[PDB]
Amino acid sequence: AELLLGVNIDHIATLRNARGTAYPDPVQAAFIAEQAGADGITVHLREDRRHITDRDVRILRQTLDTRMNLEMAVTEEMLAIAVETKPHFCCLVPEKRQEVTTEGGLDVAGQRDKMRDACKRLADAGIQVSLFIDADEEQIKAAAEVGAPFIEIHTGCYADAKTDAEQAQELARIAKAATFAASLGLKVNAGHGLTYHNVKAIAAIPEMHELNIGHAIIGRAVMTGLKDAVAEMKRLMLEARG
Amino acid sequence: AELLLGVNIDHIATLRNARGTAYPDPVQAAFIAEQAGADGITVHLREDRRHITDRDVRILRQTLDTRMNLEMAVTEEMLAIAVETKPHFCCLVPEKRQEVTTEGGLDVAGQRDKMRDACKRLADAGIQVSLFIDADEEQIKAAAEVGAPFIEIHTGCYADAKTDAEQAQELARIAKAATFAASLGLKVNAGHGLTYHNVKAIAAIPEMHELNIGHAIIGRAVMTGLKDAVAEMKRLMLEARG
Amino acid sequence: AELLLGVNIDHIATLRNARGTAYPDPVQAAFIAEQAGADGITVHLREDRRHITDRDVRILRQTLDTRMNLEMAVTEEMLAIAVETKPHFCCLVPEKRQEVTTEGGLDVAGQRDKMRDACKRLADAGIQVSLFIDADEEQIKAAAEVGAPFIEIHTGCYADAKTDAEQAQELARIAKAATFAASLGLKVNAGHGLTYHNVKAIAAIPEMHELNIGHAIIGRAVMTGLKDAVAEMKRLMLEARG
Amino acid sequence: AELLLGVNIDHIATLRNARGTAYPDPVQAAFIAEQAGADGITVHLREDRRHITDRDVRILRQTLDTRMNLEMAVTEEMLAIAVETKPHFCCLVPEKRQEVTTEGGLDVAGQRDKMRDACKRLADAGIQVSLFIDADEEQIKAAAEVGAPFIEIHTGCYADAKTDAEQAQELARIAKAATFAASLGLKVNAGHGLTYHNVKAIAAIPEMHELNIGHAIIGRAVMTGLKDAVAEMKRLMLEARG
Amino acid sequence: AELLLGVNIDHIATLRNARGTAYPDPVQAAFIAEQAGADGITVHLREDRRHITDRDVRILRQTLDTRMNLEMAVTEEMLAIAVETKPHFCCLVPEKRQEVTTEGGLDVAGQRDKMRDACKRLADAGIQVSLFIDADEEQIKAAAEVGAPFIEIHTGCYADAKTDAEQAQELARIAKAATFAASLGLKVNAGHGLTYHNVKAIAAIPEMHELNIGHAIIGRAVMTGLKDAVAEMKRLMLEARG
Amino acid sequence: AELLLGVNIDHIATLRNARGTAYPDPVQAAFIAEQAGADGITVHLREDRRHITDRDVRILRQTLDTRMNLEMAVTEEMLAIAVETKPHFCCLVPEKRQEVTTEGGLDVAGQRDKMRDACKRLADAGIQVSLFIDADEEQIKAAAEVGAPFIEIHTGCYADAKTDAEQAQELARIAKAATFAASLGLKVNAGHGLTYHNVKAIAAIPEMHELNIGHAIIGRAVMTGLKDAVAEMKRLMLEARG
Amino acid sequence: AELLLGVNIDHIATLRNARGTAYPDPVQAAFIAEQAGADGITVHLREDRRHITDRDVRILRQTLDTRMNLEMAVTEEMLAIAVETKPHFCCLVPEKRQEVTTEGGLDVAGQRDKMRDACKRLADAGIQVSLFIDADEEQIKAAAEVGAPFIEIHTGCYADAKTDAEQAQELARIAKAATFAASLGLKVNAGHGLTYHNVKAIAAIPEMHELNIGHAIIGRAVMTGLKDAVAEMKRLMLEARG
Amino acid sequence: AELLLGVNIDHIATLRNARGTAYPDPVQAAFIAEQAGADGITVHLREDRRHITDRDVRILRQTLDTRMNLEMAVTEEMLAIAVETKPHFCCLVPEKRQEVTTEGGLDVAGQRDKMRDACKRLADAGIQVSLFIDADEEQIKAAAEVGAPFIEIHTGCYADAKTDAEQAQELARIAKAATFAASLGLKVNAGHGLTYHNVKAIAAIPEMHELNIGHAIIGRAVMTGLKDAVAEMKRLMLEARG
Ligand SMILES: CC(=O)[C@@H](O)[C@H](O)COP(=O)(O)O
Ligand SMILES: CC(=O)[C@@H](O)[C@H](O)COP(=O)(O)O
Ligand SMILES: CC(=O)[C@@H](O)[C@H](O)COP(=O)(O)O
Ligand SMILES: CC(=O)[C@@H](O)[C@H](O)COP(=O)(O)O
Ligand SMILES: CC(=O)[C@@H](O)[C@H](O)COP(=O)(O)O
Ligand SMILES: CC(=O)[C@@H](O)[C@H](O)COP(=O)(O)O
């Protein structure tokens, strides 16, 4: 199957927000990424508007040349913005104000009715919803039951592995989890913590549809520039698939 | 005695600390900068270690090919770190309403004793001290008395000007402060808020010795790569001087 | 004695509008140009919206990192648009709604009343007005007489000169006129028809403040890319001022 | 099974024709494209000469290093010019602006006689003919009847698809049509609204011989330069093929 | 005064004529050069057409964006062609026993009547005529006598000098010759043999108006490409004149 | 198995010899080529020393990092030079094309005695011999009979094919000759007239071991530079084969 | 199976140590290489510290983004350093006569007890050990029984093979060895002497896990820059595995 | 006022000799440097042939496009080599303990007889000799009397300066020594230990004719490639001078 790359540009905004300036502008990064290998642009509108802001999402929706993937918390505030913005994709993730980044996966089991109503509301607006969960068989079953067509498997543990043996374990865990998801008719994506040195093993998973990568790309971009950083990532991914 | 460029790489660490990673590494950025037009490297070690860390300071002191400029608040902890680190340059600045003036500069005038002790503490360790203050006569005089060899004029107001008239007014303030400081035997630097579109007017000021710019350069770097970002700024500065 | 470059991106929209597509997007070009030597971005909102659209002006006002220069004809429609848009600059030009390009030369002396009202309404919105006129003393006096702080001398005749004698005469005319406008306290810009082979002669004119160039740059850009096209133009202008 | 790229440079003339200038010159673009991945150069000489002119065709025939594909309307004037110019390939299409012949594609089945005589007059001049038509069973059978060896499927509907579902439906219609066309002994091409984001699915169609793409490449070119724009499209195409 | 660069593309043709193929095409070389520092293109149409052919001149006259400098022998055939092609510049060169031993500049003094008619016939066509002659008193005096507006000093002996003393002596000659020609109301050009390592001394000569360099540029181009080759030469020239 | 690229740098010398200078130096071109895709370097030392000279062969044998392929005519002088030079390969070719040694490729069948001695003489010196011949049954068998290790099929007729039908025939005639030569235990190479647009069909023939290309690459280089030219050609070859 | 590239930066230090300078700094080379294709960085800390020094190791352990591979002799000093440094990998090499075989690999079979102790000590510290040995069916057995999970085949003889016959003979030797090593459960690496012209045949060996290359890459870097040098080598390797 | 750059490529050989390979080849480096800003190439033939070898000098004398500057000690072996090689320039340097001074320069004053001879012998061979001495008045006087036309001041001390005051002091010495040398009729050069960060102060010295730099450039080259390394240094030099 084909492998797509979704560039998350949140960290361009984390750099802008460090100061009250307008640069660097996520709108510019979007254009560069979309013309360098990005098949879609992902932004996570946090309730504390830590990096990406409402302004960014509003403009991006009008300038993006590819489909927008809006990552957000499952709250009334975000559900409302999502419906009005009508992005092509919507990835629901867990969120906390004092968190460094998206922690574990989203709890779909012990929160079924909440996720059921969310998927339906977004679906009515014409948005394809993806659920960001761990490589957990129980979480996978829920996602498929709440009505979500997509699920994004958290790869943070995989990328955080200390030893080669622990990494192999997380990798096998993800792969299996991805295989089962597919049997349930779920389309599977992955993301979080993927770098230039560990993306290939993940891109190798046949079931994987799109990888959403942000931090590693932006981290690389400050050195070589966004174009080469994105092109580099896409190439590695295609080499792993083919 | 032309115009030098000091590149502040704090925002490299800003991007890194955003996540729990080691990249991008300020150590790599320094090499790039030093070979693209930087005549020195600036790093601000904050009390909260927001971006630059002790590790960063410790390693950079061993890898820098050019002179190091340590930006820090006037505290015993920091003075101690500076004496141990022995950076070529040290710039004293206020940290979170710790001893700051309305405009944002260090209050040297109302803290002569504390500054006298710090400048001597650092001068005796072979460090050349600069005081970050507003383009103010009173502050300039106090910097001269305290013993500081350098002063770095706060150009944030000029950089934040909302109209051409306000910008022109701030420019004139700086130009006058630069000349007054020089008549007092001080060498004058500037920076903070400088961008690719307002840097020339400051670089044209005859008294300016070195400009320490960070945010705008890192801002451009995420798009164009650090090498072109640094080379660009340096060319603008030399065009304005020559 | 600094010489600025205003980049007119109208022809980016020309290529876009040739189809119902959204690419190439002027928003992208603006970032590229602004970081490659553009000191400002110019867009001409034609009544027929042949290239630049209302959407363009609206998004650009929000994404430009440099000042916006809004070129438009003198009509209630455009005056209202400019007032709510609050661009930094506004250049008033003659428009036929069917012309190939600005026929060059706004009749200010022949429309005193209308122009006087236009200049005041725009200035009341904090917009610095520039009148696009011919290198004619009467039209220029009329420009400063109606309030306009800026003027942009039409360089099309100079660019279209068919013989050396005709070209040198038109160059002398523009220069003579520039000096004249300056003695009136006016700020003088120039544009239309400037290319990589005739710009130097205009850049050399001491009184010139900003040159607005569009077509020649975009024409170069399709071959070499917008960044090098803009950088090339800016370098030639500065060399001429040297 | 080889997949070829035909670069249509009409829009280069579009940018030129915005003024009475000679630049940008289609002649230059041709060389750049042929050396960056173009296997042929395509030009559409419109009755109104909207972009490509008689001068362009005449000079290109003498400067092209590859093969020229002359896209034209089935008129006496064009057929005459085609025989005069003697391009390697000829692609017959409905009028421009907003067409004359029902739909986006050419009505071969409806003007069986006109085309039949057009294909023979051209084939006798040593020119290989292609008929631009919609993905339609009847239209194809008609193309085989009139004797045209080539056909080019209108990918416009596929490119304009507003939803994924709609796009996949159009893609399947194209694939089925292409397979059916080859069964009639016809060689099949395509490419009308093809872009960097939708080209792969088309290039992946086994029967496709050459994709003729113009607008997207030119729109990308104004940003990155023609060379990279053409090389980028060619790379994506071969990736989808092999 | 400013210094102009005239790029001779003859050796592009020599490369092509070696295989009698179509590439490399001088027409392509012209675009690249004109967009990288060339203020004009020079082509020598030999009667035997060793390199540049009739076809070359014919197309070039239609594609050049700058100005053509037709170098040719003083023959009725050549005169009739220059009058028809109507190049902006024309440089008369020797092809038979019209030379002056080594450092074979055109023999004007010995062919006063022939040159006189040539200059008058071409001038009536509005073609600026230049006489390629060696740095000789009498040859320079005859040039102004026959009415030639321009003269081009043969710097071949200077370029081939083996020792510093030899080169210095030749450089002095040229300098005296240029100054002497300027007094006679003559405009002076140079070229032939100039390289990246000896052009500055020539460009530093105040009287020099345009340098027409060819072979060194193309020889450089084969390694680094035309664009850079032309830009490098142009930069060296402007640095010298500075 | 794999396909190799041999770059003939003869035309670098053509451009140099055009004048009496030492640039462009084939020695430089060789390094560039060997580092951009060339797996060997080829030079044809003509008896008339038209381009490549004795100096060139002498220094190249000392500077080449890859195997040297010496193309020469069958004569005592050349045989003596080859034996002394000890290139890794030696390609025998007809010279002057107006003798009883040429008919297209080398006439081995008609000079069986001369070739037998040549192959033995060169093989004894540890040189791998290649006979440049047409895709002719008689010549191919004769090459193997004479003991030559390699043969190089003359791809000229294929490169000169006027029509698509003609080129198809020639391609088939080559493909057939290749398989036939491989069955006789001979290694088959090819070259001459191959360009960036017709090289793939040849590189696709499984039997081909190494393609030796000269003119096309140098013709591209004058525009794009040698590195690019060679890398481009190698990538195309590997795409067609691997 | 995946093929990894280990870049040995020792010769960067070779250049530095040639002078008492601090540049070129291995630390900078490591960042470059890790982002241009390196899956790991290799440094040989010699007892004499001829190039890489103790500080290089200490700093690199803290700046490397990938995995460190520490080449060292089997001594108490180095074992203590390795344990303290905790590199991901450790490759044992001969540095004295008594430790080397005639071919150049480490004499493992001759020092069973010593290597057994070494491997256990490093293994307990969490370090994966590799033994640099000859393609010998005795040293290989010794490597297994000693506990080393990895071995690195000395490809020095293969790198020196000049004739096709010698290359084939040495290659076959490495291949059989690799296959034998694998049958014993050993992981097999290679390198040493490998170049841009001989790396493919080795990379094509199925069992090869990682190639550690150094001098050839650095030698290319001085010409092209490290980034391109590393990328080129990585691309050639991956191509061999396709 | 003209400032030249002599690139010393010894360290290219240093890297090569470390493995005994043929690469990187000094001959290639020379072409790169001469085309990137080098006005000459310097090679130090060490008696022990530590880096540059006899073959290097032999080939270089034949491939250099510019002028050779052979650095060597004063010995019958080297004198003979110099006269046989015919380098444009010869720089006499110390290599034995009894030849070096306290600072590191050549002891001309102490060996006036040995130098007087060496200078005449070389001068008769047509070689311009330079004496590498410290910034010492006594050593300078001996240089003029001995007959040497050039002298190269040892900038080593200036480069190894430990403090700002210490460095400014060394700079004054050299600047005073350069002026003094000039009053004696001695042409003056310098270069040793010069880097991208300390060359300007030296280049600014009016008397300087040519700077011979090596290690700093090759150390930069390994990171960025020789072309940019040479180009960068040349630009910095011209910037300091004009
Ligand atoms: C891809 C995703 O859903 C996230 O896990 C990721 O960590 C986002 O991080 P930021 O919120 O810092 O962009
Ligand atoms: C302008 C810039 O980048 C800095 O110079 C400035 O001092 C930043 O300080 P912080 O890194 O504490 O925001
Ligand atoms: C510079 C200016 O104001 C214009 O005159 C120019 O001709 C604009 O042309 P477009 O309206 O085609 O951009
Ligand atoms: C997609 C493209 O660029 C063209 O192929 C298309 O035929 C354009 O036609 P016009 O140039 O008539 O718009
Ligand atoms: C130096 C150069 O390239 C030429 O200017 C010169 O006139 C060449 O003449 P030919 O092309 O007749 O050798
Ligand atoms: C195609 C090419 O460049 C050559 O291979 C060919 O052998 C050239 O021969 P000459 O250099 O004798 O024309």
Image: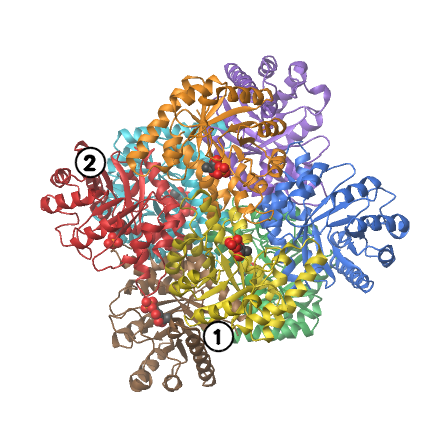
Chain colours: A cyan, B green, C brown, D red, E yellow, F orange, G purple, H blue
Find the distance from the CA under tag 2 to the CA under tag 1.
71 Å
Residue C87 in sight here: no
Query: Residue F236's spot in the image, x, y percent?
Result: 41, 36
Query: Residue C232's spot in the image, x, y percent?
Result: 47, 61
G129 or A49: nearer the eye? G129
D36 or E68: nearer the eye? E68
* Pair 2/1: label in front: 2
Query: Residue A208's spot in the image, x, y percent?
Result: 34, 34
Question: Is residue C45 depicted above or below F233 in this figure?
Answer: below
Neighbor class of circle 1 (other Cα within 10 Å; few <14, some 14-19, many 20+) is few
The reply to whether label 2 and label 1 mark residues of one chain is no
Give the labeled residue for mark 1.
B166
Q: Count of labels shown?
A: 2
Quadrant location of the N terminus of chain A in the rendered image: top left
Query: Residue A9's spot in the image, x, y percent?
Result: 40, 49
Residue E168 located left or right of residue F223: right
Question: Is residue H66 depicted above or below A135 in this figure?
Answer: below
Residue B107 in sight here: yes
C189 or B30: nearer the eye? C189
Q: Secondary structure at mark 1?
A: helix
The amino acid at mark 1 is: Glu
Q: Secondary structure at mark 2?
A: loop
Neighbor class of circle 2 (other Cα within 10 Å; few <14, some 14-19, many 20+) is many
Using the rendered view, name the quadrant where residue B121 is placed.
bottom right
The amino acid at mark 2 is: Leu
Give the labeled residue for mark 2.
D186
Quadrant location of the C terminus of chain A in the rendered image: top left
Residue A82 located left or right of residue H65: left
Label for residue B139? none
Question: Is residue A81 depicted above or below H2 in this figure?
Answer: above
